[PDB]
Amino acid sequence: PLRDGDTADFELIETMRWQPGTSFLRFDRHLARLYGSAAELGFACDPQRIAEVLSDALDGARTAMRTRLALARNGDATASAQPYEPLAADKVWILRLARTRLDSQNTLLRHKTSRRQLYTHARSEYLVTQADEVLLANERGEICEGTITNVFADFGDGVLATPRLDCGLLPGVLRAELLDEGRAEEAIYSYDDLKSAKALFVGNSLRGLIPAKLV
Ligand SMILES: [Cl-]
Ligand SMILES: [Cl-]
Ligand SMILES: [Cl-]
Ligand SMILES: [Cl-]
Ligand SMILES: [Cl-]
Image 1 (tube, protein in one colour):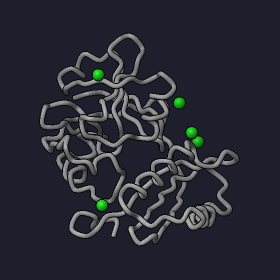
Image 2 (cartoon, helix red, strand yellow):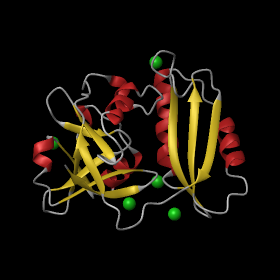
Image 3 (cartoon, helix red, strand yellow):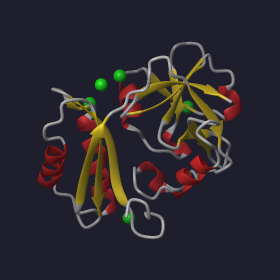
């Protein structure tokens, strides 16, 4: 069902990091997105049920957990938790550009769903040893995002320039937090422009910012 969101109907998805004591990192941002999308897309969504599955999935958790929450249009929901494996602090992810392009007019790109054909295809273009993450651009050659991350580029001034939403990408939760804190700013740029970035990162709510290098 999660693996066949392209031929069949799709599900809404949220991937979060649960932490001892403080629970899900950026929890309210995740629920805001999930509840907002369910409302816009016509998904039955019972918050009491969402809280139930999350509470059961995290019952007895002793350390950080990667938690995947999924919602089907009929209101059916699942939550899965497994130990979070953080990246070493000195780890730098290698990025490559997929030939797979996104369509800026595809409105479904602003919802995190199981309809991941484009991203799965982009990811299949490169081996793990060739790219830790694969970036996708749109019909105007503007970088949008990674298959599972948003992009943040520092062209020298300390501001994390991240692709503007109208380029065709997921408004990520980490992305949103960085924008609201004044740390990131919307911008437009190509793969080639990134070569002039003094610092580069890709990130998501689960892992935070990940230093990256373009190839
Ligand atoms: Cl938050
Ligand atoms: Cl729909
Ligand atoms: Cl942690
Ligand atoms: Cl932060
Ligand atoms: Cl702009």
